Length: 400
Length: 48
Length: 49
Image (cartoon, rainbow over all chains, first blue to last red; front, side, top):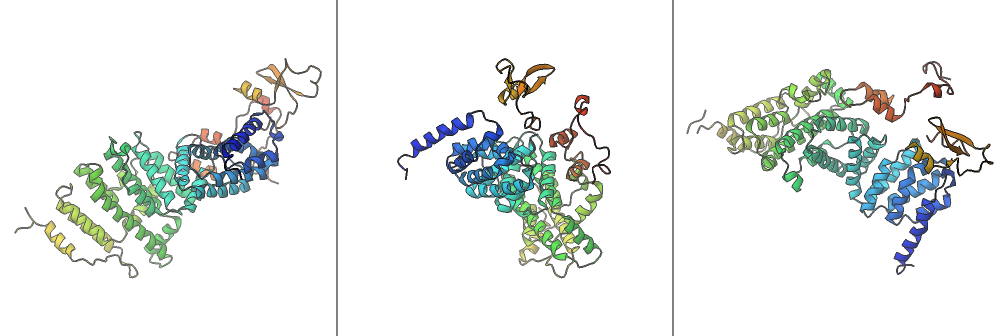
């Protein structure tokens, strides 16, 4: 009804909104009528920023709890343009802190609405929350905010989180220990309801921005990526998975499905990492043969245990043996096998045929050590694996 | 910073405030020196 | 009980007494303020109903 008068109406409203908000008032002097007016006028990003500037104290005021909640939800549902004002509003919202349990629940629902308002809200919120976590202004709501974001988007939230970890690793400073502790605790509060495979895929995806393409610690970045992948591999084990592994060690077939699904995810992640090493890693950087072999040993969990914890000392001494055994005992894939053989035969890739075939032997033996009737631990359809293996012995017709 | 925070808040410096309507309000001191008075002692103690 | 959980896992979280202060569970008390505040001797025994 005011399409022609939109600009004039908006400016005229903002005039008195600024006047009322700037007028120095005691906390009790704020009017629920004014809060309702702000809620109705949240359609403007400027109004949504002015509200979120003082929204924390408005919520803290018990007398304004319901109107302030209405204002918050209106701001969240109107924050759909993903502008600079929207980003600032998200920053203010994450700065807000709420003591009450009911208020926290309402805040979490409003955050769900905010994320639904615009798709990039998820990535922006994840970036801001992780920046706050890295900084000293930790909000006691950051962990549950990320939990709710993961609930809302079990995949895109892991993807955004993975790219943000890539941006932290590319940063000059060594964020290895901080990132390890960060993901550890995040998983702890989320109770492990995160798609580890999706997060690993997000980390695996190559970055095309000039900041990455010109990174002068590309080799260190790849090494740190491998390290954090191993840490995520560790964290994939829950208390329930630990119980299932104990039962399997004792021969009990209880909750074996959880362990089998976990191992399937582990094998898929390992296959993805091998594919990445084979294809993208040489493109990103040209690692030395020793470093490349070390990374392959890490991803296959054939590396020495010491290097895994030499940085942060995590996991504790007790957990290392159990976790290493459980992660090492996993099934194999035909794709992994053929990729290993191709990398070994690849002269340009710094992997000797003897080393590649030895690693294949070790991995095949490890998978065979996972003898299970209900699991296709060793399934291969292609017979060209035999030909590749035989070629690996060829001498440069004589074979070693 | 404390001085600025109180000035922002509903604190009135002793020079402006009416000398008469002073018994009701509660006096506020900072590092001993008297700064002013405030009508409601509550709602700022907990806030601080 | 949550806070002690993170605290006990020190040298990994970098969790600090200063971070506890920020969490605002504990606070510094001078004698002047002590003059006008009740104290609970043992929470395990006193505050309990």
